[PDB]
Each structure stands twice: as C-alpha cells, then as structure tokens.
Amino acid sequence: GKLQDVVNQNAQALNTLVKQLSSNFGAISSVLNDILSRLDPPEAEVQID
Amino acid sequence: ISNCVADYSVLYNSASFSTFKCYGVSPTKLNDLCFTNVYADSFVIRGDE
Amino acid sequence: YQPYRVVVLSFELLHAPATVCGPKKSTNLVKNKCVNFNFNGLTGTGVLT
Amino acid sequence: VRQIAPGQTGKIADYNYKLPDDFTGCVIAWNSNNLDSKGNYNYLYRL
C-alpha cells in the first residue's frame, strides 16, 4: 500500500491537468479553434489572453 | 430563416445602414460558418433607442 | 426623432448540423498532409488520417 | 466616417482606404457642405 499510493497520487495529478483543458476561464469558448474561426485578431486577442 | 446559402457580404458592404454591429462573431468571418438556425426580427423605432 | 428601421439576426454556433453557410464550395481532401481544414465551419490545423 | 477606424467593413475600408491594426496616430474629420456642394460630381470612389 505504500507503493500503490505513490502511483495513485501521480495519476490523479496528471488527470487533473488534462481536465483543465476544458475550462474557458472567462472566455467565450474553451476551444481555441472556435475562437479563431469566429473573431478577427483585434478581439480574438482578448479571448486568447 | 432556414436551409439557405446566404451571402452576408452583400449586406454590410452597402451604404444603406448606419449601424451594423455583430456580437459573438466578427463580420469578416460570417462567410465561413454554418449557423444551424437563423431568426430575423423586424420593427421600426425612433433614433435614440 | 426620425424613424429608423431595425433588423436583428440570431444564430446558434454549436457547429454540428447544417443549413446556413455562405459562398464558398468544397475542394478536395488530401490524405496525410498538414492542412488548415474546414468541415461545416469547424476549423483546425492537423493531419487527416 | 465610422469606417476610418482600425478594423472595419464596408467598401471604403475594404476597397479604398485601410488602416492597419497596430495604428498610432489621430483621425480628424469635419463637415464641409459649404465648399464641396454647388452639386460637385468629381469626387469618386471605387465600387
């Protein structure tokens, strides 16, 4: 159980990093290609930042 | 409005309109997007409102 | 105080189904080369496998 | 006059005069009905 706990803690942290790619953090979308196909680079720069 | 092939570049490139304001999209990009659903709402108001 | 005529258009950009997209037509598909693709509006850079 | 901003549509910002996105400077405009209307038809623009 001391060896399995190290494997469980590293797998839980890499899973958290992958799921953070579906937050928009206040932008209009979390997909970067949906921002670039709907806006021109003056106001697409506000959502990408 | 449904199942069209629209051409938005005929609209904004004419000097009829004193207001052409798109909100979630930029007007340059409108000729590239399939829109799923379009509604068209019309009325007459005063100049200030 | 003069009469102005107003139109309001309303889209839904959930990018899946169909029915309103503008004046450009399908070119070919190139099969294993880095492209800028476009399928019903949804864009992206990648390789088509 | 509203089309002499950095990033616009219309046929004077797409066919006649275009400002860059990273523009530094001032845009100055005033109505001149006294001098350019008799009226005057020698002011052209691309269509």
Image: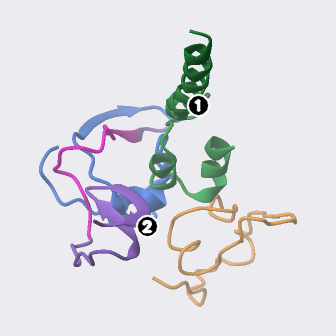
Chain colours: A green, B blue, C purple, D orange
Where is residue A37 drawn, in percent x and y? 45, 55
**Which residue: 54% across, 25% down?**
A11
Instruction: Residue B1 in the image: state x and y as whole percent.
Output: 17, 43
The residue nearer to you, when weighing D18 against C22, is C22
Q: How many marks?
A: 2
Could you tell me how far apart the alpha carbons at marks 2 and 1 are, in whole angstroms? 46 Å
Q: Quadrant of residue A6?
A: top right
Q: Residue at x 53, y 35 (%)?
A: A21
Q: Is residue C45 above or below residue A11?
A: below
From the viewer's perspective, tell me whether residue D43 is left or right of residue C47: right
- Residue shown at 29%/36% (left/top)? B42
Judged by its main secondary structure, the magenta piece is: loop
> Which residues are the magenta region?
C5-23
Query: Residue type at mark 1?
Result: Leu
SS category of the residue bearing label 1: helix
B19 relative to C27 in the view: left or right: right
Question: Is A22 in front, or is B23?
Answer: A22
Q: Residue furthest left?
A: B3
Which residue ends up furthest to the right in the rendered image? D25
Residue D15 in sight here: yes
Circle 1 chain: A
SS class, disc 2? loop
Using the image, tell me which numbered label, if any, was put on residue B13: 2
Is residue D22 placed above or below B43 in the rendered structure? below
Q: Looking at numbered disc 2 in the image, what kind of residue is underneath it?
A: Asn
Residue topped by disc 1: A17
Most foreground residue, B28 or D15: B28
Position in image of residue A1 (x %, y %): 56, 9
Horizontal arrangement in the rendering, residue A2 relative to residue C26 (left or right): right
